[PDB]
Image 1 (cartoon, rainbow, N blue to C red):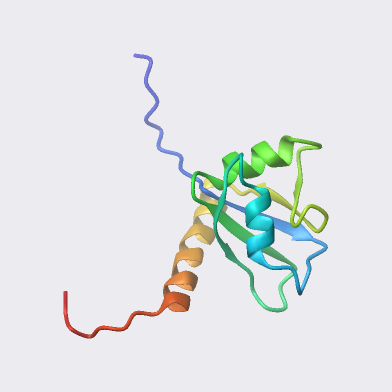
Image 2 (cartoon, rainbow, N blue to C red):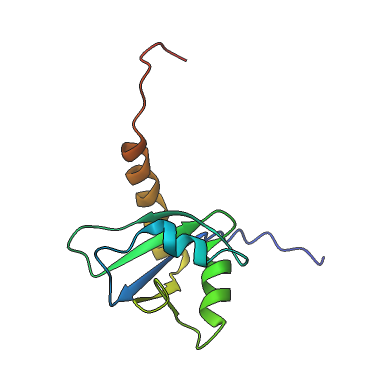
Length: 113
């Protein structure tokens, strides 16, 4: 056989711990470059952590960059540690991340299509 079809996607990772309030996503998103760039970050006001899906794979850039040292990646290089959730928990956040960005971008047309 030699073939994998189990179907297990997970391009979103989350981090929790010391979180900053002024830092910006542009600064941390650039740090994950050269090893998985960030595609989007969803943080809830008053939350204790945050999730970030990458353009190539959060589990890849997060577990790869998270592994670069101890195995837990910190956010902003000294703030929150991120770890990929499970198929059930990783997906629950993946869907919420889409609904959050869909409302942040908004659409102006009403023409149809």
